[PDB]
Image (cartoon, coloured by chain):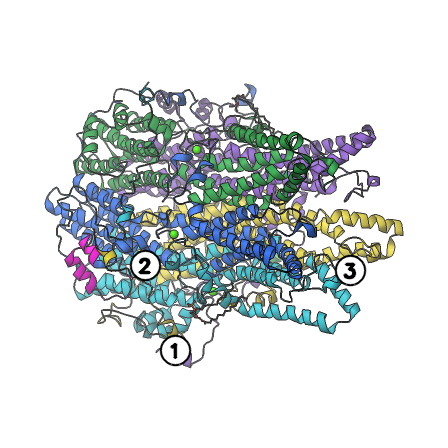
Chain colours: A purple, B yellow, C cyan, D blue, E green
Amino acid sequence: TVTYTARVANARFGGFSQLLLLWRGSIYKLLWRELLCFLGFYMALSAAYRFVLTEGQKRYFEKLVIYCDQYASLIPVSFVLGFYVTLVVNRWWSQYLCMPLPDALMCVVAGTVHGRDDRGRLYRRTLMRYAGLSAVLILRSVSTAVFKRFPTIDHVVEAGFMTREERKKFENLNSSYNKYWVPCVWFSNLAAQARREGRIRDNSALKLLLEELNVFRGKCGMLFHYDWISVPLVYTQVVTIALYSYFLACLIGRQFLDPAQGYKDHDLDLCVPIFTLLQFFFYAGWLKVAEQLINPFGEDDDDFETNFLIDRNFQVSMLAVDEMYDDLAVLEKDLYWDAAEARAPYTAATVFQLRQPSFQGSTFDITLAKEDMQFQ
Amino acid sequence: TVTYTARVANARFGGFSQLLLLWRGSIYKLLWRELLCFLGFYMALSAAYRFVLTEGQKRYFEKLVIYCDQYASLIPVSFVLGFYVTLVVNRWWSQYLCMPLPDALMCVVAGTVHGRDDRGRLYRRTLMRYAGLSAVLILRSVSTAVFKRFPTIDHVVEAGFMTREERKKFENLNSSYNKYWVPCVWFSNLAAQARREGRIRDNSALKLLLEELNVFRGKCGMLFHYDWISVPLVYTQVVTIALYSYFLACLIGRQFLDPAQGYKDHDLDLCVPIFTLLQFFFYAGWLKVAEQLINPFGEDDDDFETNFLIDRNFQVSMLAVDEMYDDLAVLEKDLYWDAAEARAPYTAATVFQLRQPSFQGSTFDITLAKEDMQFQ
Amino acid sequence: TVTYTARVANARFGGFSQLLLLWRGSIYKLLWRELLCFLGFYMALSAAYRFVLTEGQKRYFEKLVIYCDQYASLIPVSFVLGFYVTLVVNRWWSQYLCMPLPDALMCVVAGTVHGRDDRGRLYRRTLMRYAGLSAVLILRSVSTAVFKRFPTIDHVVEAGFMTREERKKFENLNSSYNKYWVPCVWFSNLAAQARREGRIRDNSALKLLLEELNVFRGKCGMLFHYDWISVPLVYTQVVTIALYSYFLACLIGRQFLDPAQGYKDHDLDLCVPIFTLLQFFFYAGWLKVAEQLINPFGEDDDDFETNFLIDRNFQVSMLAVDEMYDDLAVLEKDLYWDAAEARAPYTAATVFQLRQPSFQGSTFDITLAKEDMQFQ
Amino acid sequence: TVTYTARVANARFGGFSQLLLLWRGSIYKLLWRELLCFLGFYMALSAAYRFVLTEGQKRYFEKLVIYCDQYASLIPVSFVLGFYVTLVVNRWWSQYLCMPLPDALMCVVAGTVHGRDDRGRLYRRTLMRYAGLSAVLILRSVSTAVFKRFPTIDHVVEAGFMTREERKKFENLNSSYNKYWVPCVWFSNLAAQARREGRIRDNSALKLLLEELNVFRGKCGMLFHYDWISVPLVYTQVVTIALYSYFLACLIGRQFLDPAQGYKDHDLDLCVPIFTLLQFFFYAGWLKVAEQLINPFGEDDDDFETNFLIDRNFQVSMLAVDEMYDDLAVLEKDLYWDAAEARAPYTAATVFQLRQPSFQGSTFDITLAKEDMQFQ
Amino acid sequence: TVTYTARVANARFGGFSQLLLLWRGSIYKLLWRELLCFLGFYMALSAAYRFVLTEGQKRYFEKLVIYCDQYASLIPVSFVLGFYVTLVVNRWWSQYLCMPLPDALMCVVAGTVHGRDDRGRLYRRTLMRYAGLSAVLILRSVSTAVFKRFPTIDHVVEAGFMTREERKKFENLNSSYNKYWVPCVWFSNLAAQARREGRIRDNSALKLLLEELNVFRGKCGMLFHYDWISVPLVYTQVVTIALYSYFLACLIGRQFLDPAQGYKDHDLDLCVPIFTLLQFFFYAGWLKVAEQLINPFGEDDDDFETNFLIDRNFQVSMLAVDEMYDDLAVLEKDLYWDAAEARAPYTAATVFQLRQPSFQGSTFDITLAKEDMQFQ
Ligand SMILES: [Ca+2]
Ligand SMILES: [Ca+2]
Ligand SMILES: [Ca+2]
Ligand SMILES: [Ca+2]
Ligand SMILES: [Ca+2]
Ligand SMILES: [Cl-]
């Protein structure tokens, strides 16, 4: 993930122009090799036309350039790229939202699984660890970074997500299918056991835990589904073929011809196709948007920071359900106890935000006449 | 936020034309500097062509202008801008909907956390304050205005959202990750304690509170996610490059050439490219839509009024759970107690809305024949 | 709201052509003034060119017309209008869906708040009235029609939505922010009181009421949010400027020039720009779609009938929770008690719908071979 | 509804070409009259030009044809049709999803409303019948087919959905608004009564029934909303005007002119405008998509089969809650009781689907090196 | 399903170019027959023009080619294909998400339906089997692969999803409509019976089971709805006609004419229309995207692997509710019990992901001045 939110807080004169100076996660880093290849092919053709071809060969080359320039139809490739890239971007955001987060479960577990003794701590920590373990098993299945961090289940055990006894039970299960779901079943069984032992004090609490477990588990399953059901290969091939067809038509049709021949719209030889290179950057970068986002669990600069999320989720979940269990500051009167109204102070830098009228609704400046307001 | 809803209540002859006279949050305020820069570059080129260049240099300049005018392809930039700006606008609205609001929690707390004594007031106020505190911690993390108002946790304490004892516990937590979630865990623990003490009278009430806490907390988390996962930098760079490429092609290709040379479509010298300036305003403003909306938590005119929302939310939540707790007007018979039907009166200005038929459904004017209506 | 659903039940030969004959909520009613203004400007220019200008002035005018006709680029304005109008239409439907309806609450209240005595009737009627009152307070804040009907809180009291004692409590609340939410807090308190008194017989019933109260209250809040957060002014200005730029280019470039001058594509003088007028109707009407829908709570023909909805909602809610409480027809055997199957009769006009095969699924005509169906 | 799912199970060489041979619900059936009218107007103009007009009149006609052919701008009409038709299609699917189905309620009622005696059967059947009755009342309000089947409430009574006593109560209710919601209030009251009598054994069961009742009732309400709030008439008029403007420009500008006059791009007289007729079919059919779908509750071939759904829903709901109540096959061990794993057999026709590797995740072929996998 | 997620983990120099080398689920496999047919027709016309036609016939053929090349309007077909294919792709993903999965139910059943004895195992296995059976009945109704695997209900019985006694009850039900829903009613009855016998220990548990049953059943129903309500046939016909019209215009208008005739833009005879073939591949493949996805339950390479999902779902559900019931590893202290913080180790290949700063929010680099931060 390349975060530039702070740079674009305000619409400024520099605006996105300053974003054009960034390298990490940039169009430049993704496209410079393809740009050099396109320029190399173009300049090889230009050099052959200028120095190698005979007069007859040059005349035929000019006819082919004029013919090919007709098929450089940008409007259709723009259509398909717009639709396809928008599909990939929407799917990318949907995939991010399917990342399993323990926050809802950790709040419910902290509020529902009780006891300051070691057994209560074991119940809470084990429930949150099962959630973390499911997340790790699915992520190592779908994320190259996570897999490289956990290339075998032995690494999951050594990392503390799974115990050796848990690993014995996990491997003894006869299944040819991915077992990311197993810790969710463990969670359900352990929650039922906690309710049976009175650690969960009510049936409604157990229902809430199971409701939140299924939300978490469904997010894990959604990651599996996105990983399995690629964007249809035919669609990806269609868009790639359209883009490369346009690039072929430009590579031939955008050649600078001898101005002496006096061909229509060929009277200037700049020797470098500046606007064609800008068009190539535009269109190829537009497709590179999809190329980077189509699998966001790789190691691209703008791919999701899955290992960071595993670490954050585990650390925060353990804090919430172990260190913060029943550890409230004493109930005390707040600063605004004696004030019927309340408003926090403003800094010198933000007090200007005051004196903007408190919006009440769009209708409170109509100012009707007396006779109009009387009920029938 | 620049609210103009009242101005556009009706489709009028003036309509959006009157909106063209607004300055705050306007295209003009966002784009006048870029418009002056574009006009300056254009007029510098025009002045060099008219007064500096020699005849040969002028002929070459005319060839370059004619060549460059071919690549001013507006249709592709329109495509990419449409798709990209629509993505940014949808994301902007989604981000607004993720703003944490205490209204659902304040209704549930007012209805479920009981006692007119000081301890009941402490429970209700502390629960709502925890919600407000989570909102402040995330907003100061994602909003420049809120951060400038709360540049340190000391400011949060002095503003009354967090207590000194709460601050001690908050800082003692060993976490390298953002702690906006901590008050939600405090809320869960305090709700469990209130249920244990009988302040919350039923398990279903506690479940409802925890359900609403997780909705609120999820909105906080969503703000964090939007702040972290920028719109992919490559996509922003692609659209910016497309727009600036079109601007380069226009800056060269829209130059007024000497009509004496008799170039095709160059026979009028207006000395000011009026339609190119209007196109620049159109396209650059279209992108400025995204530039303003890409981070709605800045200090732009149309950015969200986050400090106003913090103040409103805190004040209303405290009113709802403290002043309005168990403070009902006595149950009394309403004006329409003795009327089988009921309808409120209309004013002289609105009685015309009556005599419009009460819509019953689209099918109640078919008026079939007698023989058609008989069951088989 | 202009309902034409009945006219378009079937795709007919007349089809939408007949819709072109409608006036209420029509393109004609919204655009005839702008059409006359455009035609007036066009004909003023035409008259000046034909009768006022000298020969030299006419030649310069012809050059300006030919120059301006080049910038009448409809493809870009089509893009921006498509994206912007689609955004406004989607937002319009979303706003309609945020209209608070008491139906869910009235069903729950009728089923959960018990007693045929006056006190039960008071509880049920007061709960539904609180819902209605919240809807009225928000609608009068966001709707010009509703505001004109309830220009002051005194009108809300005289209309029966709020009692005088309720008004005393309502005004005594020290809040600078809109108080539409207050009756929802009253509802929560009154539901808690009803549960405490045994009028609500179970905790799950109270939870259901509070769950439905928050859905209703959230819809009220959503109306406030839509009213406050306009479609970004910059975007509206951009689309308006694009449309008016195209109109300027057409007003100059579509002038009929003297055919004697023999300009390319200027050999016919129809004296009335029929196709330009049709294009103006098309594009200006396309934008008028957004102009009408951007604020659907005004007094346009196709704006929402908010006063009708207030009346319907109040009347139906009171019927449901008061007249229909515990007023069931005696449980009796239905017409199909003794029939294992069942099907209602068809009329002579609809019996043709029978003899269409009952769809079972797409796979039930594959008709595989014997050898293929045997399990391995 | 015209179901062709079976014909398009696989992408085949014939593919959609075979779909071009279908008549029911076809473009041909919807558009042949308009195609004949367009061809008649075109051929009338052609005949007048070829046989009636004088030489001078023919020269003026040629100038008008050349002028009109310039305004046949397909790109703008394509834009507006794309956006508008996509809106109508999305709304069409949304409306289908709002069709009230009793399946969720019938499962809950079968599982929660108890007793094999006549009184239990009466409770279950009456609850499901109330759901069916609400569906019939709304559908007869919004569907021409259903209305023709139930043109009066007397038909609803004779069909068995409503009883005579129920009809007395239904008509005695003083409401000027549609009463489709009344049976939902009856359902709520009857569910409360069943809980009070112990037929519903728990408060959570009653809550579940009321939760599912409100989902069903909300779908009924959504049908009412879609029926009432048409797609804005101005938008429909705008798209229709754009299409008909293009058709006018084609009807004049696509006339075959005398090749002898040697007009540019007029050298071939085919006497039948084949490509213009194909364009008319394309664009007019594109709009006919919306014309058919804008009200899906009519009697078009592809309109929803509402009467079939009423019959299916009633029959299945009665089966589920009456014949299938507490009628389980005895709990017996399944075929895979003694198998730790399990997999159903494959047929000779489907066994080829085996030997495709069981997908485990995208990361399980990375095959890292030994040194890379060691924890830090 | 053709999964290529692993190939596109990173945006690479090869990128989608390497995807152009794939055959299974490729554009090539779907389109080579149509490409050969188009090329055959084109070359037949070319051969007739070059070798069969007389001089007069060749001149007329040249006029027809020039005339037809004018109507090869790609911009409109691009529009309709974009909108239509996007609709089909969104519907395809929606259909995938409606595939019934037992995971949520298996977690709830494992946690709520109790007993290590044979009767508990029978309850859990039978509930999960009912879910699997409903999925099989709907899938065999909508999926050609599943139907070929289960061409009769006898195959469902022999496969173990349905028992012989269950089959007797199933066939005795008098219904002309699809019975996929029957096992869901069986599930509801059996869950009620388990609650009555005390196997389900609480009312909230039973509610949770019924809530998850209805989610599962609704997904089954959604598959039925998608199977029944095809994408409107008129829309499919419109897009197909537009594409084939463009193909006709290209087949005639893209013919290579004799360069000697000196027609404008006809001076090169390549004898093979390379760019027209690439355009045909682009557009025909774009439509083949929809052709494959319109019914994803067929036997295309990229159609859903429904039989694999049936096998996986059944096997995993049985494991979860039978082998894993109350089979927890003993509660033991985790690796991070004594650590206030926690972080799993990194491998040599992934440790580089560390030293990237832990994102705290976009506002934590503003660095305001001292005087600005002071509260008013
Ligand atoms: Ca990637
Ligand atoms: Ca901003
Ligand atoms: Ca309006
Ligand atoms: Ca219809
Ligand atoms: Ca298929
Ligand atoms: Cl619940």
Q: Which residues, given as a range, are shown in magenta?
A: D154-179
Q: In what quadrant of the picture does the C terminus of chain D appear?
A: top right
Quadrant of the rendered image containing residue E234: top left
Q: Nearer the viewer, residue A151 or B2?
A: B2
Local crowd at mark 1 within 10 Å, few (<14), some, or many (≥20)?
some
User: Which residue, given by chain and number where applicable, does mark 3 sit on?
Assistant: B268
Horizontal and vertical percent position of residue C133: 34, 66
First in residue order: circle 2 vs circle 1: 1
Q: Residue at x 89, y 52 (%)?
A: B55
Q: CA distance from mark 3 to mark 1?
A: 60 Å
Q: Earlier in the sequence, mark 3 or mark 2?
A: 3
> Which image quadrant: the N terminus of chain D?
top left
Q: Which residue is mark 2?
A: B363
Task: Report whether the residue tagged 1 is closer than 8 Å to ligand 3.
Answer: no
Residue E36 shown left or right of residue E105 in the figure: right
Q: Quadrant of residue B31?
A: bottom right
How much space separates mark 2 and mark 1, taking CA atoms?
33 Å
> Which residue position holds label 1?
B348
The chain holding disc 1 is: B
Subunit of label 3: B
Q: Amino acid at mark 2?
A: Thr
Say what secondary structure mark 1 lies in.
Answer: loop
Q: Crowding near pointer 3: few (<14 within 10 Å), some, many (20+)? A: some
